[PDB]
Length: 49
Length: 49
Ligand SMILES: *[C@@H]1O[C@H](CO)[C@@H](O)[C@H](O)[C@H]1NC(C)=O
Image (cartoon, rainbow over all chains, first blue to last red; front, side, top):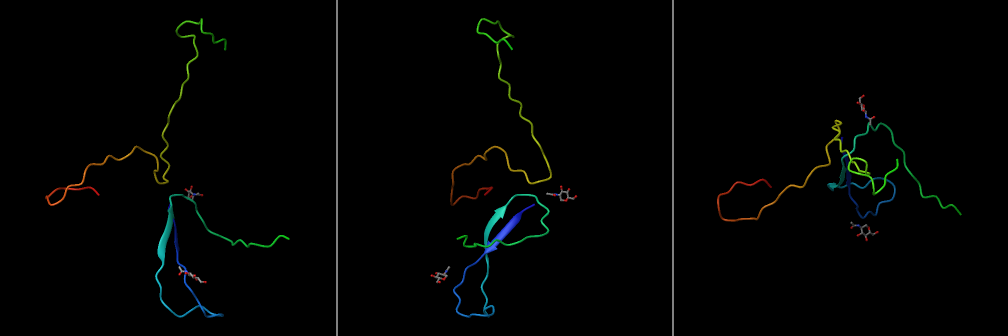
């Protein structure tokens, strides 16, 4: 019944693949809501012009 | 209804609000504030932080 979101931001210089390093993720927000989440998507910021 | 100031007791308009409490298995979120006291130091006391 709790939705947890953790987040972290890092400066990067490598192009193609994920960087090889270690860095923990801090808690960002907790939400007290009850849903039976099973699938998700993603949203894009298209330039409607 | 024909509510009027000249109407006697029992005929005048009365505003009524009924409060009911729901306990779905989702986490409880609504209730009264928790009291607080002062902070004491250097004395063996019991606490509820
Ligand atoms: C999730 O599934 C359980 C099991 O049937 C059900 O009791 C509950 O209401 C469901 N919750 C949602 C948000 O669909």
